[PDB]
Amino acid sequence: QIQARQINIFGIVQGVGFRPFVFNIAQKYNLKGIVYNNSSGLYIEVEGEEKDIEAFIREIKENPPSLSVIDEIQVREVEVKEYKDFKIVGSKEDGGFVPVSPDMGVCEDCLRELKDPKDRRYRYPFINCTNCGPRFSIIEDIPYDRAKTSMKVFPMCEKCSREYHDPHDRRFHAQPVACFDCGPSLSFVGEGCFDDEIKCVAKALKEGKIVAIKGIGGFHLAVNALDDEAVATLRRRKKRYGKPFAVMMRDVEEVKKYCIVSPEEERLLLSQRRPIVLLKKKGEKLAKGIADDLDTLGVMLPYAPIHYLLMEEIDFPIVMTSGNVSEEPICKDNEEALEKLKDIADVFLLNNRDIVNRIDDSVTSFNAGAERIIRRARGYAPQPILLKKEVKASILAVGGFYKNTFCMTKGHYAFISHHIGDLDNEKAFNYYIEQIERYKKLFRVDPEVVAHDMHKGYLSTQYAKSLDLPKIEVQHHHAHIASCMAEHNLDEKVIGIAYDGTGYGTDGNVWGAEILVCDLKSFERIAHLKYKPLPGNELAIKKIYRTALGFIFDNISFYKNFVEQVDSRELDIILKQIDRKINTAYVSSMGRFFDAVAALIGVRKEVLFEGQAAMELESLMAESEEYYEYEILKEDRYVIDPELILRQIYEDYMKGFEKSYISAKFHNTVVNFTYDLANLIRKETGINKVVLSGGSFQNRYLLRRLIEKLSLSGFEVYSNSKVPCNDGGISLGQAVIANKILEG
Ligand SMILES: [Fe+3]
Ligand SMILES: [Zn+2]
Ligand SMILES: [Zn+2]
């Protein structure tokens, strides 16, 4: 017997080698039929053995082409039609852009040619073809063409030229084609070294030195991830970091030794997008100082020819952290890196190919049955987000402050930028401004309106106000909810749960623990945490014991052991400044709530970076169904007093309960009261769609447990997946809100 199916794939499917893929996996499972493009995405007709079609449907479902963004797959039964063969058939929809693709990791064919001793490009560190290599990182302008890339200064040799022009070659119109004879080459700076440049880097790593490596999107810093001393000297030389290091490993087998790797996680690792994937550790096997006191590790695989070559010369994982002092934009030019990283790196691996657009490594993960991206950069940007509704007019969304991205709309596309970083330094600002001009140029966008955060002290806000265009201001947490709404094409009233550290509220106070009823044009504040004073504002976020004190300010005597640990003079002044309202904001913030908890139970008195106590509190928790009592009090809106929950936490602490146990109980309390609020709002409003966004949802337990709880009570639950739930996704939300305000 023979079985026949008709398959529709909706989403971004062009420009990603999807059709040649379908053709190949057709010859694989020996199937007959056709594939072609349509307006919605792709059309497939397939017939053959029942075991081949279910597997075909699985390969498309489980490992589709890396650069594709599949939104929906539909399968219907159809009558057998007896096809002779399989064909890639054309359509009026053929040649459907996007003009600029993300940078791509080395493809399987280039890998095999890199490792083939008989191949002219054997060991060539800049090998690429039509299906891989640098794209965005070297592109100045459009249409995509060598002359409009940093490859224009290299004249092609004969051998590369005929490959480029041969329509049946895998390097046909491969713009950055190269070989040893005509292409870029590597250089080694530092101490003398006789060998080839990769071997030198291997030697330097082996000796416990820091190597600055020029990759695709910029420079990165590497040491031997098994060498405690080398990791320690990098920690000392950055000195202002604290953040965990990402690590590069040679293959999935090596990852499975250090981390838990599910199939979806393996798909993200092996993807040509090649991101860092945050993974659960399997027992401490790496050096101290990589990712201490945390149960997760960011792992990436090789992505450029240089890494594959490096991997056969070393037998240890390597730290691969951004090439910057502190946290400013990473270096991109040779001379810029040699100066900026002089006190960090011992040696450098350079090359003579300009990086035009610097772009950081992406950082992603898998949780609650979907990809949850933390930092959307190399391999993802500058691919647009697909919108169901055509945008009325072109909007520039300037984003926010932390982990900034900007966003431009045109047609059915939201062109969100790659991760820019914190807009709090000259270097970040230039990078930002510069890249706005580049995106405008690459995607032919001329913005008519500007959307910005309500906060007046953001560089992004100041920039918006400095432009000569109508301005729409957007509340921070509304933009979080909306950013998720854009992903899932929602355009109706939802229950929006916006939990994060901070964002300017419409009442003038800090928000970040809000339940909103909102659509794309407006919102209503329905619920938040009871305001507590944050004495010293910014300082209290580093010294989180101050946040604790702010939360417990009207009930100091209850927390005897904790308050007696604080210097008496400081305590007096902290308590007086709250009374006199000096340098003190009032906050409704999930990030601060967590910080207070962390401080009270001796996890952390002071943090090296924002969110450290939040991440550690999550890592140390035990398995527990238990939780703390809470009262939902109805005032002007629905409010919960965090101090009443802190009371019980401190009690448990004083009785000698484990931090692991208390952390778990706290996590369940937030989940439980949030669920209870969501039910109250649904009961009043009739709204059954819930959106979860804001940085707090980077917490795996929080997101997972809440999606489960709400789904099991009939909620239709949505959270970020294509853009981050952190401030990296804000711009997308700003854009869709601005569009909706214009529309009517
Ligand atoms: Fe935020
Ligand atoms: Zn290739
Ligand atoms: Zn050549």
Image (cartoon, rainbow, N blue to C red):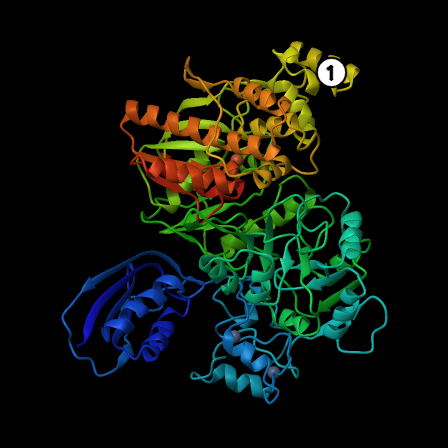
Q: How many marks?
A: 1
Q: Position of residue 233 (x, y in %)?
A: 80, 52
**Can see residue 398?**
no
Question: In front: 15, or 700?
Answer: 700
> Does residue 241 appear left or right of residue 462 in this picture?
right
Residue farthest to the left?
79
- On screen, residue 176 above or below 11: below
- On screen, residue 644 above or below 269: above
Quick check: is the Cβ at mark 1 less than 8 Å away from ligand 1?
no
Residue farthest to the bottom?
118
- Where is residue 543, by image quadrant? top right
Which residue lies at the image location 68% right of the left edge and 56% below the top edge?
A: 286
- Where is residue 651, by image quadrant? top right
Question: In front: 37, or 541?
Answer: 541
Q: Position of residue 502 (x, y in %)?
A: 56, 30
Amino acid type indicated by mark 1: Leu
**Can see residue 448?**
yes
* Quadrant of the image containing the N terminus: bottom left
Which residue lies at the image location 56% right of the left edge and 33% below the top edge?
A: 661
Q: Position of residue 733 (x, y in %)?
A: 44, 40
> Does residue 643 appear left or right of residue 331 in this picture?
left
Question: In front: 661, or 92?
Answer: 661
